[PDB]
Image (cartoon, rainbow over all chains, first blue to last red):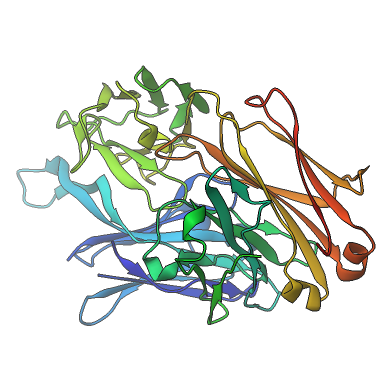
Length: 234
Length: 217
């Protein structure tokens, strides 16, 4: 996987710089809210070619650093259409000769070369960019405590309500990544506060409620906040 | 140079036939014989991998159940024995004509056995209450199919439209669905009542199931 820069909320009209970090053709794809995957842009490994989709010409700029480790997507004049998860990925292309056009005289020496996209294989985890005039906020986290009202047979359920934050996304781990099975993190819903909220629940054996410690780890990059909450039985 | 994709939804019984089609408008075959179309799968939380390249060639770590077919303008991704892991959104992508475009995707849903949900309920924390707010959470766990009714009752007095429902991606392993229904009130409004109840109607249950709790108790 390729490590990408952190999620951000951006003002309408401003610009975002998204990083992508392991030579390779580098493509920028995106997924807008309620939309299919969309091709934004690419930089050729040769460094000859930079290009974009039609709606992006004038707004986008692709760079990569001197030591060629990190690639860079600048996108300017942000609108609410530009609210998306932006993926960087590496690509394989064929650079083929389509035809040649020459004359005996030694004047005309055309030969057409074009690039043809074979594939995009290794993708970045993605960078969520939300366009909004609203200020960012870290989340309030509350225990969804295991009770008799959350047990089925010998299976108790517990978790963490993550609430009143902006913007997306938050990342919810459990016991610092140790506990990874049986976890449901629901897609957030925008509340009437214009802030997000979701629950992360875990199903576990009820005979662990005294024995095992359960702690939700909530990460919000745009607000520079991490919240650890321990969840105890009622 | 749009590359329209059909169907828009595809239900499959695990162990049985999946097929989907990418259909371009201009041709995709270069003069070298190669068709520049790729197939990608995308599990909803996660980055897309590459399944098929050059129309027919499987990428690394792609099992032989995924087969690529087609030429020129017509293409077909075929899955011959569907595992629950194949629950994802599938995208075609043409690489011949500028600019390179994605299809709008095909969603694969797995039709499994009917599963009744586990119904749970969580009172608001005293900590959240101190902050002036009460969220009451109903949890629907591991059920099929996705269609379910959640109905809030307060002191057996029956609410409308103060609840927010959220539902998960279909499970990659169990092909089940899981749902949350959250009721959010001011602390005063929450304190004005005692009994909070989540009434759940699902197919797996002959009877609607109510999970209730008495505030302060």
